[PDB]
Amino acid sequence: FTVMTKMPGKETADRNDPYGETGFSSIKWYYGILVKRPERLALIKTVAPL
Amino acid sequence: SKLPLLTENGGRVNRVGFTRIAREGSIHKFGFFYEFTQESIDFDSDDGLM
């Protein structure tokens, strides 16, 4: 996970907000899997009681 | 109606400008003279004329 946080202040003060009144926090990542032996993944599909 | 009010979101609001002025003055030239003869000094009654 890559987390980027900028708090209000001179960090967020630019030509679009000279006063730097706002901040933000974001998170991002990459994910993926490679299925090598799909037959070894066994699944049963059924209904369930209330 | 023209107070620089500011909200919690800031933004491009309440921009101002400035001005300056230039002053000037110049100099001028003056003078005058007078003329005399040798006799007007030597033969005059008053030896302190000049």
Image (tube, rainbow, N blue to C red):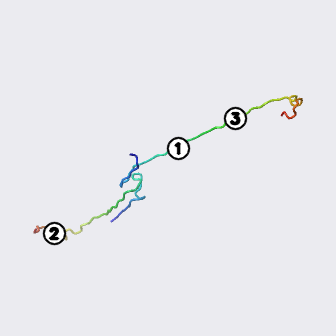
Q: CA distance from mark 3 to mark 1?
A: 31 Å
Note whether B31 is above or below B15 in the view shown: above
Residue at numbered disc 2: A43
Q: Which chain is home to disc 2?
A: A
Above or below B9: residue B26: above
Query: Can you tell which mark lies on residue B20?
Result: 1
Give the class, few, some or many, for how many residues have Cα within 10 Å of label 1's Cα (few <14, many ≥20).
few
Q: Name the residue type under label 2.
A: Leu
Q: Please, which chain is the residue tagged with disc 1 on?
A: B
- Residue B9 occupies which quadrant of the picture? bottom left
Residue at 54% x, 42% y: name it: B21
Question: Is the C-beta separation of discs 3 and 1 under 8 Å?
Answer: no
Q: Nearer the viewer, residue A36 or A29?
A: A29
Q: Label 3, on which residue?
A: B29
Q: Quadrant of the C terminus of chain B?
A: top right
* Image marks 3 and 2: residues in contact by CB distance under 8 Å: no
SS category of the residue bearing label 3: loop
Q: Which mark is residue A23?
A: none
Report the amino acid beneath label 1: Arg
